[PDB]
Image: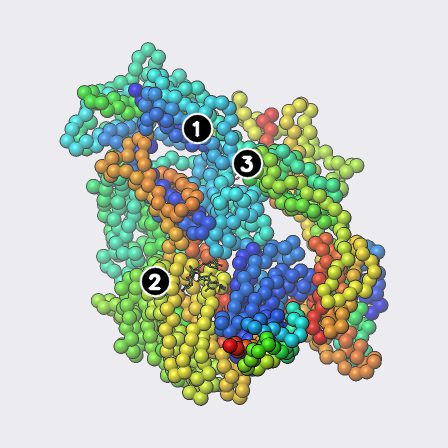
Amino acid sequence: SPMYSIITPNILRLESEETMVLEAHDAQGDVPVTVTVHDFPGKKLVLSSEKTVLTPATNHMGNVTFTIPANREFKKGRNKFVTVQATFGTQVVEKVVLVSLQSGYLFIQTDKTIYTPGSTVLYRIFTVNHKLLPVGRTVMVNIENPEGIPVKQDSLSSQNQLGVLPLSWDIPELVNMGQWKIRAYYENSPQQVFSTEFEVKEYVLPSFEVIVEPTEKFYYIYNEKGLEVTITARFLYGKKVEGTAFVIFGIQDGEQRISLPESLKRIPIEDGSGEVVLSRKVLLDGVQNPRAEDLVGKSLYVSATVILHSGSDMVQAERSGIPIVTSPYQIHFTKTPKYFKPGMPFDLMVFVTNPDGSPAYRVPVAVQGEDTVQSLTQGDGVAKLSINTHPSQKPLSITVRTKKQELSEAEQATRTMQALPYSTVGNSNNYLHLSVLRTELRPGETLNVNFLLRMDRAHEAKIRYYTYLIMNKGRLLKAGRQVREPGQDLVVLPLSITTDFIPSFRLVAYYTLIGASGQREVVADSVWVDVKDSCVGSLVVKSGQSEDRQPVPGQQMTLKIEGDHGARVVLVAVDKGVFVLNKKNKLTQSKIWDVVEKADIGCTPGSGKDYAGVFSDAGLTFTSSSGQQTAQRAELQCPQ
Amino acid sequence: EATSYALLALLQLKDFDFVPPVVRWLNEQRYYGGGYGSTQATFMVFQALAQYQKDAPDHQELNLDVSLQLPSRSSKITHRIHWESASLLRSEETKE
Amino acid sequence: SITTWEILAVSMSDKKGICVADPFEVTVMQDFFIDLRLPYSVVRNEQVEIRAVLYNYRQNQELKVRVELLHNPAFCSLATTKRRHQQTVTIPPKSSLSVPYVIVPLKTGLQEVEVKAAVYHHFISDGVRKSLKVVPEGIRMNKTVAVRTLDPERLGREGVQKEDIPPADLSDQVPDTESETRILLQGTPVAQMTEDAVDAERLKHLIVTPSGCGEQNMIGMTPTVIAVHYLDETEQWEKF
Amino acid sequence: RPCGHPGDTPFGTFTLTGGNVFEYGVKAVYTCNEGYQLLGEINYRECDTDGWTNDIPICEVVKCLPVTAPENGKIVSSAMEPDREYHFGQAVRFVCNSGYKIEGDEEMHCSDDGFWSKEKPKCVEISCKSPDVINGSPISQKIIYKENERFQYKCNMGYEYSERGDAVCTESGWRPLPSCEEK
Amino acid sequence: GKCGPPPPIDNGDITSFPLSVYAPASSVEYQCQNLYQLEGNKRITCRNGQWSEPPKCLHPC
Ligand SMILES: *[C@@H]1O[C@H](CO)[C@@H](O[C@@H]2O[C@H](CO)[C@@H](O[C@@H]3O[C@H](CO[C@@H]4O[C@H](CO)[C@@H](O)[C@H](O)[C@@H]4O)[C@@H](O)[C@H](O[C@@H]4O[C@H](CO)[C@@H](O)[C@H](O)[C@@H]4O)[C@@H]3O)[C@H](O)[C@H]2NC(C)=O)[C@H](O)[C@H]1NC(C)=O
Ligand SMILES: *[C@@H]1O[C@H](CO)[C@@H](O[C@@H]2O[C@H](CO)[C@@H](O)[C@H](O)[C@H]2NC(C)=O)[C@H](O)[C@H]1NC(C)=O
Ligand SMILES: [Ca+2]
């Protein structure tokens, strides 16, 4: 009757703090628990060994926090595993867990994006763990030429550096031009290699910027007006630009570019602005295909050369990747769970984007046949569509279309998905549904987690609590219990959102009982919640002086920097001309959270085909003493 | 069974020049043990292969020492070419 | 510099982690300044024209300006040690003026150009001093002098291998204008000597439950024990 | 009469003393970055009637005296040239030969004080004492064990072995910890 | 789950000598002082790493 269960992340990382939650449901008294982690399969060393007690005051639920040292015992190469062994009294529950070699994260920041032969590249390597907290480890750095050959190795230490490692590499005078790379990796994890590029080239600053901006972010193939483009030229110090611009158009097909010589135009740049139209006739005449439908799927690129009236500076700029499309939108189901609970409300996270991939704001979407279920995309281009599922085992097929008014039906975007029934233990029709209002969540608020139960009433009184777990950045952030009274179908969990939930977290909750043929049954459900991407703390740089005072060459200025107490701030001032030449590989905050999310162990928006699939797909391994456990995971990478 | 015993003997005498032909023939038999009176032939063939993957030697040792030795006295460039940095391009310039 | 600076900040706290601040832009400007547009490089002894553009960004105030090109022995212009290169121009308000200077680089290397300007009747002056690269007349070329295989244990005597490298051709070489010969050493790895392990799937049948008497028990125990011993060594429990 | 910008030195910042703009009578004191020493005595620049004072200071990174491989040990880290000046930041590792175990700090990096962060360790012969098995008594009578030697033991009444029933002497210590579980 | 030392009561003690760890199902008895009266079950039992309820001693006058 008593059931001991352990949950551990799908993949365990080295030198990272990992939590393990221990439960002894339907038990009395104190239960001594000793958790030991051994290597697989030899068990030569005891990587961890902690102890705890499950008391009735804690509802027989505890956790074990352990950090596995990066021992010299682990061996491309074969994948490594560990044996997790939890001992409750007499009973022992073991699970074989996959191990990732990633020690944490390395971020490289170069002062500039492009460099002249002879100059020095100043770069900082930030060394953190999976919690983004500064650590002191040994890092291997490789300088790599455009050809690919490493030309300078080094092994330094991050200790006593507050997670910031200042380095430099001198560029020889005689050097090969092109895209160079810096490759760093932790000493303990030579398989996790982080990279940043910087171009090496002979150049001079253009002293001004040219902006090629199309009216629309795309080109409708049946628009007789053609592609109207506005040219905006301005000096690097703000003032507008007077001059002449040579604009020419081209059609891009994959990697094959075909210039359109007939579309070449010379226009005056007056007051820093000019306009030039590519006529549809010239476009069709330029390509040797009368059938305009074939141009759909291809893109357009525009090249503009602006010359000042003084004739002392010239800037060429380009805007490529302008898709020739037949619809202003594009529907994706990459954020909607692919499993539903028959009879319970099914939530869809429609992701409507512009042809260039950017989110689309205020776009009407609806389900075919259900005009009542018509929602509007938010600022992130994500809309929520709640439907009512009928209790059935039929595959739920959904087709979502855009209902943007003032847009014809031929140009409306459409996409079709399918969801499968959540198979239950012994066809008992016991389902759990966690629902959350889909809206940009920010640190410092509170989210109401609605636990909704559906099962027969013959065993509904036995369910007295739910076990909920939170997954953030690939590690167990928080676990607890939710008391539920007999008769209540819906209970509300006030979950306090702090800074530890950035950028997103998964909430997987489950309940257990003894039902049907006296069988031990587990029913689970998970949901993915996004949070407003931002810094954990804050860092703002603003003017530390009067804004009547104008900056003058050489003049002292006061810089107001406001951030977290004790934090080490590293600075860099870059001329905007550099970014006019190359604006790639620039370190932003959005890119940091991007890397974190790509090292996530979850692979689905939510739920699964069974109670084990919910844990496995949400990056968790459940293993009970009675035998109910999740299947093994032998894949570091998610399934395609 | 006999060929398995002989392979175990070659792994004890460190005669790694005669081992590859033996092992290749063993793999060509596709004998996976099991069956009526397979006891000896099952134990020995897998014991010998397990011992072959144990005494398995990694890669041919790489350790080059290349010294530019010029008659005039100046600074001396020495080079240690190791396995871990074999691909590292080591450039040395001379103006004359 | 007369431009806009982008200042980027990154903070690292023990309790707060990493934070990349938003870029803070700081534009720097003056009412009156010189924009000296210099090329990346110039060929020795070749006459080039540069332009110094004088900008007057006052709303409704004209400026009588004097602009001078400093003398430099490394360049050739009308500016000598005795006489100056001045011109008194008038730049209308909210306007600009371009002053062409014709120079001839005389000696190679990082040479310096300096242009100054001062206005009459006002306390407003500016100077610009920039550098440019002067490059030999010829074109950058490289010759593959030698490609030799290094193998002391195979091609060397007594464990040492001595390779003699011939001097480069350098027949069309510009007098002086030195050269640099690169000796590029790289290692040749091997790593091959290991036999293919027995496939893990072909062993699924050796896991048998032992039974029988004193002799049959060992008949059933042998395949299972030997199976674990092999799968443990080859580390194939992933596929098994 | 203003002077020019006093110019920046590699790996070093400067502050102005006695004023706030590069005018006559200001001092520009320089201070090198962390890990870089102020090479020389010229540490300031005074804007005078003609210009700034003598020279512009030079910063250089501190260096550590190279360390050799200990007796019966090797150095398996850092890079390229051997026995060259290791400067601030560079780390190194020690790995004893087969049959020798490390006894000290395994890694160390070049510190700020031109010295190493940790001391040079030793390579000592692999040695295992006779383990004290809890709730059990040893079977073998040997006290000192060399590498790979097996240590036989039995569990007392009311107990039995857990997994492995013997212990092997390896470099990091006994691989199977002699443990006894309840029957 | 074994138990630990038995809990002390007021004006009373255990009849035997205390041990550090008690196996499951072990039991020890209690006894009040002279003229004190014991109320409840004089025996406690080790169940699930926890002893049962100890008796109380009634104060005389
Ligand atoms: C694993 O299991 C442990 C069990 O202890 C969990 O630790 C709980 O984590 C809480 C995070 O939400 C922490 O609560 C905090 O406690 C603050 C006090 O700081 C303590 O200082 C002592 C030093 O004597 C340390 O040992 C403690 O660890 C704490 O750091 C409080 O200011 C604050 O609030 C409290 O809890 C509730 C909140 O509603 C209040 O009502 C209450 O009055 C109290 O003020 C803060 O929330 C704390 O570490 C601990 N709390 C409890 C009750 O055990 C881990 O979080 C678990 N880890 C995982 C991954 O599940
Ligand atoms: C000298 O170095 C250059 C490095 O760019 C090598 O590359 C070629 O460079 C020439 C111009 O010098 C161009 O034809 C191409 O950019 C490159 N050609 C090829 C086929 O890759 C060049 O090969 C080197 N020469 C020698 C003799 O080593
Ligand atoms: Ca997010």
**Residue on which disc 1 sits:** D30
Q: Amino acid at mark 1?
A: Tyr
Q: Which residue is mark 3?
A: D112
Chain to which mark 2 belongs: A
Amino acid beneath label 2: Glu
- Label 3 beta carbon within 8 A of ligand 1: no
Disc 2 target residue: A445
Q: Which of the 4 image quarters holds residue D142?
A: bottom right
Quarter holding ligand 1: bottom left
Question: Is residue A418 toward the left or the right of residue A219 in the image?
Answer: right
Q: Which residue appears at 70% of the width and 70% of the height? A: D181
Contact flag, marks 3 and 2 (Cβ < 8 Å): no
* Circles 2 and 1 on the same chain: no
Check chain identity for marks 3 and 2: say if they share one.
no
Residue E11 position, x and y percent, is 56, 73
Are the two marked residues, 1 and 3, in contact with CB atoms closer than 8 angstroms?
A: no
The residue nearer to you, when weighing E12 against D19, is: E12
Q: Quadrant of residue C108?
A: top left
* x and y percentages locating residue C132 in the rendered image: 40, 27
Determine whether label 2 and label 1 are within 8 Å by CB: no
Task: State which tag comes first along the sequence, 1 or 3.
Answer: 1
Give, as a three-letter code, the residue at label 3.
Answer: Asp
Q: Badge 3 sits on which subunit?
A: D
